[PDB]
Image (cartoon, coloured by chain):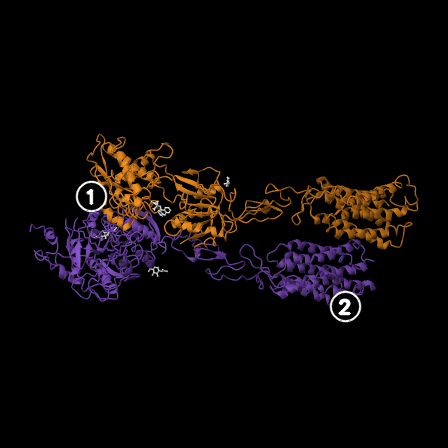
Chain colours: A purple, B orange
Amino acid sequence: REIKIEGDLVLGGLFPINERINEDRGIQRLEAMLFAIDEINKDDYLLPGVKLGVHILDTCSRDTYALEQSLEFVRASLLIAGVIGGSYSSVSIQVANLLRLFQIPQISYASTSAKLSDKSRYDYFARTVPPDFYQAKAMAEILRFFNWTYVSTVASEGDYGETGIEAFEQEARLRNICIATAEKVGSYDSVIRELLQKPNARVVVLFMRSDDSRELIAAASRANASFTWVASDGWGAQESIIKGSEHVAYGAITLELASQPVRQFDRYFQSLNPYNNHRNPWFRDFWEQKFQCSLLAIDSSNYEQESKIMFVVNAVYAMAHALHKMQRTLCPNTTKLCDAMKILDGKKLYKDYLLKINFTAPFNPNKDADSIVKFDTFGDGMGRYNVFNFQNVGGKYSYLKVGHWAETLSLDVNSIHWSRNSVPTSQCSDPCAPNEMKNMQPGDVCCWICIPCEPYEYLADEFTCMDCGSGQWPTADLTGCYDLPEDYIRWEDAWAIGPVTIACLGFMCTCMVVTVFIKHNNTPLVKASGRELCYILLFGVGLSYCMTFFFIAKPSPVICALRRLGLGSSFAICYSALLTKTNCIARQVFICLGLILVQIVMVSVWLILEAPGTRRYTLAEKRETVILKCNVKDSSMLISLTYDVILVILCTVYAFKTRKCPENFNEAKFIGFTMYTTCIIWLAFLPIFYVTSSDYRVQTTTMCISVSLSGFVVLGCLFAPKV
Amino acid sequence: REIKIEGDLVLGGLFPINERINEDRGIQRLEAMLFAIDEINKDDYLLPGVKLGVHILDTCSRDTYALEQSLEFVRASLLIAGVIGGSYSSVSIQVANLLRLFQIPQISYASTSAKLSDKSRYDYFARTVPPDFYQAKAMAEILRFFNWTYVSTVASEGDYGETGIEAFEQEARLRNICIATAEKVGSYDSVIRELLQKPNARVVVLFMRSDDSRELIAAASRANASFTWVASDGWGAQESIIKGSEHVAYGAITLELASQPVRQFDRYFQSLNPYNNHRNPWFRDFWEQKFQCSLLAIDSSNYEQESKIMFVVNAVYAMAHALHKMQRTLCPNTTKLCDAMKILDGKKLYKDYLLKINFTAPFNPNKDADSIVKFDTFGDGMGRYNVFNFQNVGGKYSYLKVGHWAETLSLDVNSIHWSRNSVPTSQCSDPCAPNEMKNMQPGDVCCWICIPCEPYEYLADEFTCMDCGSGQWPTADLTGCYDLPEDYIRWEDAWAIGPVTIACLGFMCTCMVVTVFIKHNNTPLVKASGRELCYILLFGVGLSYCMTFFFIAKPSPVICALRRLGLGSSFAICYSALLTKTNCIARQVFICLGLILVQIVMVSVWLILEAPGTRRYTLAEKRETVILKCNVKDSSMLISLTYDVILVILCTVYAFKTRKCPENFNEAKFIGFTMYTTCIIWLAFLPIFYVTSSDYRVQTTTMCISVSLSGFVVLGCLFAPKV
Ligand SMILES: N[C@](CC1c2ccccc2Oc2ccccc21)(C(=O)O)[C@H]1C[C@@H]1C(=O)O
Ligand SMILES: N[C@](CC1c2ccccc2Oc2ccccc21)(C(=O)O)[C@H]1C[C@@H]1C(=O)O
Ligand SMILES: *[C@@H]1O[C@H](CO)[C@@H](O)[C@H](O)[C@H]1NC(C)=O
Ligand SMILES: *[C@@H]1O[C@H](CO)[C@@H](O)[C@H](O)[C@H]1NC(C)=O
C-alpha cells in the first residue's frame, strides 16, 4: 500500500511497516521521514524552487518481499534520485545488488553490517551509522588504556558475533592484547564451566546478541562467580538484560550510539490524530493496534520517542544538500529544472559531490563539535558512542553515563568498580623482581617467565642476563657491576707474625759477625781464614733476611722490581762465597778468582731485568678470585732460580773429599756438614713453592731457614768457644 | 522485437542481432538455438510430454540496453527455468548481477571471461567454454616440456591481456619458468626496440588482442629480426594476422578451441528461405543485408558455418537433461506437469542436479572420448584446444594442425621449426663444465654463474665445492678424490749414491782393526793399551755406518723401530769407550768401571722404546705434501740425542791435561786432538738437523763423518807406521 506524493523530483523510501504493525523500529520512523520533507519543501533556506515529492513502500523485513517491491522504483528508467533506507542488514544487502545496476545511489539510515563497506562490490551505498567493525577498534583501544592486556572472549553464532570477533582479534594484535579462550554460543550454562579453567583471565569481552546474552547472565547467577563485564552493543542501555542479577552483573561497561533526539518532532508527532492525517495509508491502521480498540489520542505518556529518529532526519538531509549543490553549481541562474536536471546521471552525482559533503544537523546546537555530518571514503559516518556503566549508587541498578568518545577515549575516570574498588589487571606472567631478571618470553608472546640468573651476572636486557666480566662481582642491579681488588696481606693475618720474628735472626746475623770483623781480627783463626773474604761471605745473609720483606710486604711494581731482583743475590752468597774459599782450601794469591764468578749468573738477570711483567696482574679462579700481584709466571721465578741450585750443586763436591782432613780446628765438620745441610733446605722448599695460596712461609720462612743455618752451623762454630 | 513461442515450460535466450545485422557471431547462432528445440520437442528419446517453448530477445551488445530487456524475463515472478547465453563478456556480467537475485540459473554458450568463475559472487552461472585462465596453464606446461625456461612476454591493454598475463606469471613460477621483460601495448614499433635488449630471451609469449597483434607483426617486418612466436588465442587460425609476413612470422604455434561442427545443421540452415520462415522476426530483415538487395537463396558457397554452433546446441542440452532428471526423479509416474513443477525452486535445481551432469553431445561419434559434456565444480567445461602451427610446407603459409591436448600435452613432435630446424633453448645461464663446477645461483633463481673452484677441491654439490681432505688430490670429477703417498727414496735419487760409498769406510772399518785384534796382539803397544777394551771401543763404528742404512732405507715401522734405536748406541762408543780409557790413563784393575756406564743413558731409551709413535705419519705443507714417514717429532729425536752430546761434553776435559805428556808414542797427539775433532762435527750437524727436506746427508753422511774421523785420526795413527 504505497503512497506516491508528486513533486519536481521525488525521493523513495523503504521502512518496516510489518512484523502486525511495528511501532518501535517501524512506523515511528516513517512518520519522521515524512516530517523532514514538510520542512525542506517549506523552509526556503535550502532548495527554493524544486518541490520535493515522496514515494515510499513497505519493506516487510522479508528480502524477496522487498525485491518484488523494488522494481516498481526502477520501472521509470517519478524519476528518483536515490532511495532512502534499508532498515535491517539483510534487506539492505538485497537493494544494494539491484541499485548498483542502475547507477543510482543509496543512503540507509540505520543498517550497520560490515559486509556493506566492501565498496569493490557496492559503488552506490553510503550509510550514516558507523560500521560495527569500529567497536572492534573501540574496546581494543581502551584495554591498552587500562593495561588489562590478557582477555577471554565469547561470541554469538550467526552474523553478529563471527564478524566482530574475527575483526576483534586482528584489531587487537596491533595493540598488544593477548587472548586466552574463544567460545561460541549456539553450552547452556556449562559455557562458564569451560571459562573458569583460565582463572587469571578475568576480563570477559562480551560481543553478543540480545537475547542470547540473557541466558548467560541469568545462568551466571547459578555459579555466582562474577567478573568484569566489558560488553559490546548487545547490552546497550537495556534494563531487561540485567533483569535481576544486580549482585551478579555488578561492575560493567557497555557501548551504545549517541543521538540527541529532536525536540520539536514530539511537537510534530504527538500532534497527529487519525482524523487529520489523510497523507498516510497507515495512521488509520496503526490506531487499532496501538490501543487494541475496535475504533483517545497520543499523549506524552505513551510516546517514548525512538533513539534513531535523528538518524533518518540526519540522513535525508545528506541528499538534499547534495542536490542544492547540483541545482546551483551544475545550473547557475536557474532555480527550477534547467534541462540538465532531465537526465540526472547518478555516477557524477554520488562519486562527485555527495561522497564528501559537510554540513550541520537540524535542531541541535554546537555546530562545530558533533553535528558535522561527515563521511569517510567508504560511505560510513564517524563513530559517536557512549560508554555507559552499571556503577550502582545503591538504588538498585542506576545505569550511569561516564562519558563518550569519537576518535580517542574521553572517559570520566571514576568508574572501574570490580569487587569494591578494584582495577584488575588480569595479567598472566606477572613480571618479577630484578632478583629474577631473566623475564624472557619462552615460546609465545605476552606471557614471559622470570628466572634468577647467574650470581656473577647482571641482566643484559629485560629478558637477557650476562656476566659483567672476569674479576668484578655484579652491582645491586643490572648497572655497572663492580671492580675487583687483590689480597692485601699488609697486616698480620697470622702471616706477618712469623717472619717479623725471623728477621731478628737476620738482625742478629750482622751482630755477632761484626765482632770479629774489626775488633777481633787478631784471633789465631781469624788470620787462618779469609778475614777480608768473610765480610763478603756473610753480608748476603742479611740480604736473604731482607728480600723476604722486600718482596712480601704488599703488591707493588717496585716490590716486584725487588721481588725478581731479590732472589738473584741469594745463591752467589750461598755458593760462590762458599765454593771459591773451599777449592784453595782443597789443596793464597789465587783467592781473587772468586770475585768475578759472582757476576756470572747475576749479570744475566740484568738482561731479563726489563723483559717480563713488572706491575701487576689478577688471576681468576672459579668465579671469585683476583690476585696475581705481579704479572709473572709461577715457573718464571722458579726458572729464574734454576741456575741458583745449579751453582750450589757443586757445593757438596768438596764436602766428600775434606770430610775427614781438617786444615783447622773444626773446618771439616762445621763447614763439611754445612753444605750437606745447605742443600737439604734448598731442595726441600723447591717443589712446595709451586703449590701454595698464601705463599708467604714457603717464600719468607724457607729463605731465612737457609739464612739461619748458614752462619750458625758453619760460621758460628768457629767463634762459639772463642769468646 | 522478441518472439515468445509458448510451451509447457519456456526457455529464454539472449543473442547479438545488432551491431546492422551480425551474421558471423550473431543470427547464425540464433538460428541454431531454434534448431535444437525443433529436435528436442520432437525426438521422444529425451523429454516426452512437456513441450518446450522459447522466448528470446535482442541483446544488441550494449550492457544497459541488455538490462532494459532482461526484466521482461523476470516480470513473471511464461515462467522460465533459466536463460541461455550471454554472448560477450560484458553482457554476461550484467545478467549475472540480476539473475542471482531471483535464484534462477544461467548457461552462457561462449562467454569466456575470468571474473565469471568467482562463484562467491555468482552462485548461478555455469558456462560451457573454458575460462581463459587455462591458457595460462596450457602454454606454461609445454615450455617445461620443451625446456625453454627463460621467456619474454607481451600483453595487450584492457581486459584480455592484464587478466591472462597476471595469471600467466603465477602459473609459471610453479613450473620453473623465468620471465625477463614485460611490455604493455596501448610503442608503435619501438616495442621491439625495448625487446632486443635481452637477446638470450628468444621465446616471445604473445598474449594479445586481435588487431593490436597485427600492428606488431606488420611492424616486425621493419626490423626483420624473427623469433619463435608462441601465441595465445589472439592468433587463432586467422589467416589475416599473418597477412604478408610469412618470411617474418615463420615458425609459430598458436591455440584455438576445438569444435567438430554439426553436419545436418547445414542440412537445416541452408534449407531456409524467407518465404517459409514465419517463426522468426529477423529472417526477413537479414535477407536484405545478406545481399544488399532491395527485395536468390542460401547456397553452400556463402554459408561458411560458424565455429561455435556446436557450443550452443551443446549447452542448450545441458538444461534439457537436467530437467528430464527432474520430471522423473522429482515426480515419478508423472510425465506431464505433476504440480511439483509449478513452483520450480531454482536453488534445488542448479546446485543439486545440473552442476555435475554427464552425457553426450548430439551428432558426433566417440561417445566416451571427447563428447562427455562434463562440468567442474565452478561451472566451466573442460578445455579441448588445438595446437595449430605455421609450419609452411612451402605453398605460402599452410596453417598446420599438429594435434591437440585436454589435460596433458599430446603433440605430434615434428613441428619445432625456428630457423631451419632449431629448438632454441633461450636459456640464460648455460651451465658449464665440471671444470667450472660452482654453478651457483648468485642472487636470483634460474640464472646461475659457473666458477672454477679450488684445484685441491671437488664439487660438493651442483653449486658447492669443497676440498676432499688433507693429503689427497681431487679426482677427475667430484667423486671420491684420491689417496696421498709418501716420499719413496729407495732408489738412487742422487741420495743413495753418497752413503753407499761412505759405507765402504764402514766396511773398511772392521778390516784394518781386525788385524791387531787376534793375530797382532804381540805388538809392543798392543799390550800397552786396552787390547780387550779396543774391540768394544771400535765395534760401534760399524753401528754408525749401519744405523744410516738401518734408518734411511725406506719408510717402515720396523725402520722407525731401528731409527729411534739406531742413534742410542752411537755416543757411548763416542764417549764411554773413550772417556773411561782416558781417566785411568790420566793417573789397571779399575778399567772395569767403564762397562756399566754404557747402560746409563742406553737403558733409559728402553723405557721410551714403546712410548712415541712407531708406524708412520704424513706432514702437510701448502696443499701438496704427505711425508712424515714415522710419527715422531723433529725435536723428539733431537732431544733423544740431547744426552748424547752431553756424555761427550766431558770428552774434551782430559784433552787439555794430557795435551803435552804422552804416556805412549803418540797417545797425546792422536787421541788428544781426536776429542777436539770429535766434538767439532758433533756440534756441527746439530743445528742443521732441524732444517732439511731430503734429510739424508745431514743424517747419513754426518754420522759416517764422525765414524771415519774416529778410527782413522785416533786409532789408525797407532798402527799406521806399525805395519
Ligand atoms: N541495525 C540493526 C542491528 C542488528 C543488531 C542490533 C543489536 C544487536 C545485535 C544486532 O545484530 C545485527 C547483525 C548484523 C547486522 C545488524 C544487526 C539491524 O537489525 O539490522 C538493528 C538496529 C536495527 C533495528 O532494530 O531497527
Ligand atoms: N567470447 C569472446 C572472447 C573475447 C576475445 C576473443 C578473442 C580474442 C580476444 C578477446 O577479448 C576478450 C576479453 C574478455 C572476454 C572475452 C573476450 C567475447 O567477445 O566475449 C568472443 C568469442 C565471442 C564472440 O566473438 O562472439
Ligand atoms: C597501564 O594502565 C594503567 C591503568 O591505570 C595506566 O594508568 C598506566 O599509565 C598504563 N601504563 C602504561 C605503560 O601504558
Ligand atoms: C628438456 O627439454 C627437452 C626438449 O626436447 C626434452 O627432450 C628433455 O626431456 C627435457 N629434459 C628435462 C630434464 O626435462
Q: Where is residue A550 in the image (x, y as percent from the top left)?
A: 64, 64
Q: Mark 1 points at which residue?
A: B76
Tell me the mark number nearer the camera, choosing from 2 and 1: 1
In which quarter of the view is residue A695 placed?
A: bottom right
Disc number at residue A520? 2
Mark 1, Cα crowd under 10 Å, few <14 / some 14-19 / many 20+, is few
Quarter holding the N terminus of chain B is top left
Q: Residue A621, can we see it?
A: yes
| Left or right position of A413 against B712 | left
Q: Where is residue A408 in the image (x, y as percent from the top left)?
A: 31, 61
Apparent side of residue B300 relative to residue B499 in the rendered image (left or right): left
- Same chain for mark 2 and mark 1? The answer is no
SS state under label 1: loop
Establish if B334 lies above or below A564.
above
Q: Is mark 2 within 8 Å of ligand 3?
A: no
Of B163 and A644, nearer the camera is B163
